Amino acid sequence: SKGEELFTGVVPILVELDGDVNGHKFSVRGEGEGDATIGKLTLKFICTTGKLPVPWPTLVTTLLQCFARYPDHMKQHDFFKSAMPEGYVQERTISFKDDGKYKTRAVVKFEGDTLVNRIELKGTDFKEDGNILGHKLEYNFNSHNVYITATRGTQKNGIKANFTVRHNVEDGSVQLADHYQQNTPIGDGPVLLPDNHYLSYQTVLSKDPNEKRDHMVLLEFVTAAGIT
Image (cartoon, rainbow, N blue to C red; front, top):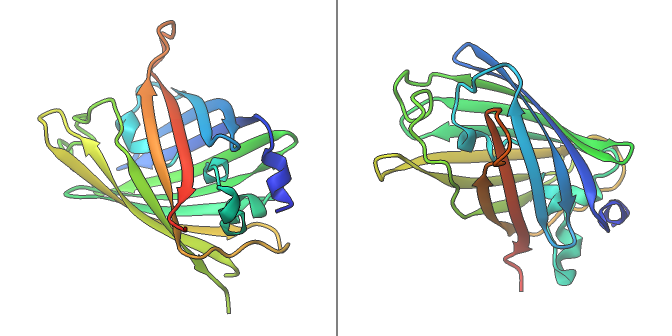
């Protein structure tokens, strides 16, 4: 409700990811803006260590839920903003159906006027010619609901989420990626504990027609729902 105030207009965003997949080290950097009042993100990413060793779509979910639009009747259930300035840790296991897993840890917080997402990612046990290390995913995204639940302490008060992403494969098939999420507040200020509900995501991947670097332009539309 107080952190709510930080998102009344357009907010500039920085993103830094450092990764290791099956020993291949790599880095991503991105910037853009978010407008929680209309639930939109825009971001551009570059790979700063050379060739990206995993497909861009596999990173979309790792590379800002505080930018969801929560409808009026649901503002009490927005943990994400109620955790700002000061932020939250966002942890995930992303399991790929017949392939490796990513473990991710992010710090999401304000630094001055900028909202920062800094992430470590460890990827293990991928197949050399799977859909991931073999770069066989299509450059597009599908639509998914992120299911959120509360969780008190006895850590401290945070949330959990779960959901399954569906990656389109070259050959017409689908590559499932199951996500299991934990979010813990950085500070000790009051945060809001939500009833069960979900975030509906819609996502577009494109290119900048004038950019020679291997990159990704990500557009996200996010609205909270699932409570009348």
